[PDB]
Length: 344
Ligand SMILES: NC(=O)c1ccc[n+]([C@@H]2O[C@H](COP(=O)([O-])OP(=O)(O)OC[C@H]3O[C@@H](n4cnc5c(N)ncnc54)[C@H](O)[C@@H]3O)[C@@H](O)[C@H]2O)c1
Ligand SMILES: Cc1cc(NC(=O)NCCC(=O)Nc2ccncc2)no1
Image (cartoon, rainbow, N blue to C red; front, top):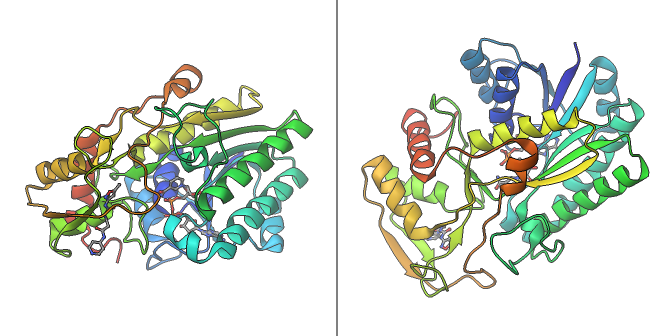
């Protein structure tokens, strides 16, 4: 019985991916330090306790920090892993500008320690959950895997790019390593049960949490940062992927490892961007509520449009996103109605 290690598996994308692993016939072991996840009333995170109910299957779980070398060494002795899916990290773009050293420590030192322990136990199969912010500001659209990387505008994006480079160098040095790097933008929606979803976040990377709070009556109006961009309706165009489609993409990457693929890089996305006004309109339709907005000045450094081309993932992973904007909103709204303050 070889297992799949999911780091950061209590969090938003991780919990959905643990569910998809169980549905695809894998045996998951999760590690998390609860930096940004909710504890349940027993040993499991609440997200994972609910995953067990949804699937009828067990999730093994260890509370630990990826920065703890001794804890990681013990973990790889206790369990026999075939692969690792790596989500443990800090990910709030706005926070990374204020506290860059925390981002570099957790993301870079954590990942380096993970890679070293993997090597030491002969586990040379990795899915790395990257960010399409590694492309920097678009030079052409949609962004494909040939687009320049490294022009990054904030410490979070830099940390993701640096990790990618370290993995590419590892794979150059040892051709027996297989690693899939997945680049995407903004996860939204929730499992269709409504029982798991994104918990309330301190510093969101996208507008949908704010929109969801306006719709339930906890904020007055969405601030729209600029309506004079070179876009169809003047508001910013951004890339949103349903978290369930994203989680399935991570399973497709895991399967690709078995082909002895070496180092591969794929974008995940729907292939179409959505404006601020489109997102507002879709949530109004899903929720049946009015969502007031106020146009304010642009945020310094924002671009008109940014979205990814997912064509390579279709060709080489056999993967497409099936769930569109209306479904993202419907599934988000269901999670909010059933869990207005998240797991708490
Ligand atoms: N949410 C996004 O906007 C987005 C976009 C692109 C990529 N990502 C990537 O996805 C991953 C997770 O995203 P998410 O949105 O599910 O966030 P999340 O915060 O919900 O999940 C990350 C999990 O990692 C845990 N964690 C953090 N530091 C840890 C540490 N030192 N040791 C152990 N566990 C630790 C947190 O407690 C949390 O449960 C990260 O790799 C992130 O860079 C996120
Ligand atoms: C590309 C883009 C995004 C965007 N708007 C957005 O993300 N808004 C969410 C945050 C927000 O409204 N904050 C806020 C509101 C009121 N008082 C204080 C803070 N506009 O363009």
